[PDB]
Image (cartoon, rainbow over all chains, first blue to last red; front, side):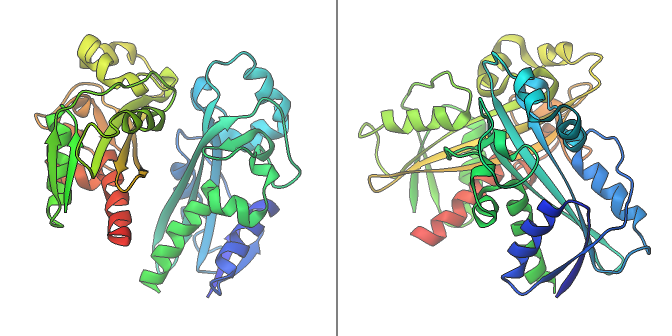
Length: 184
Length: 184
């Protein structure tokens, strides 16, 4: 089955296509820019996005929003993870986190899927901590400073299959795949 | 199958017994006090607890820790939810949350299970927001000031079966039940 994934993030592209790939699902990366609202929650942004790509994109379609939520920083950068990454970078988070007693954080991914006059949401969350220094050469964004719970390596020290086994995006994709086999 | 649940929380007792009940699992509430460490994470407390109830309690056994983590309060009261509830109460949280732009919070439950020279952990999380006033007559603890995402009612406006369908504890119990059918 084919799914059109509206995104300009190539790191997301690969994670999604490869995972859903090995069950025979072809993921097709369309680049149609859509509006991401400011909101307290990722799902709010996804809802708005699907509603807007109504009848401008081939169906079935999916979109995704994700973020790193840092406990001692009251959820920052959260919904604005992409912006904060490109402005202040990995060094900015590490500077903010210097001397922190609490380095806990989570990644959250929310997938929106549209098919048959209807939208469905799936989500995934991985808990962890912010590393004391950047490590690793894979992945994208905050991957080099996030170590998920139970692991010693950062997200960026792992391969796509390895991240997908542990990551927020992997879990939302799982929840999504579970719904798909039950509804198609 | 019988499971010995070491706890003095009768609200937890009922939720757990009833849910696992309807699949023919008899949950037995033993009261053996054990030590809960201060820790950044619920799972840390559970691990320590199981390790300590080693060979003092009949097997198989389970224990649970849970907490309400309030975003704008940097995860408070979190691991210390039970203490904070009995000291400052529902009124204390509401006072702390007055004028808050961000009322987001989550409940997390972690179940520890011991059987066959081995411990296993399961967890569940429900996202939501702190209500502006207390509502409802069911449940325990912060139930009257927590509204889970997608709902209009607080945890305390719902029945046990209704909370179990939506709650953190219900989700950990589900994850636990899924593991049980696969391993017994």
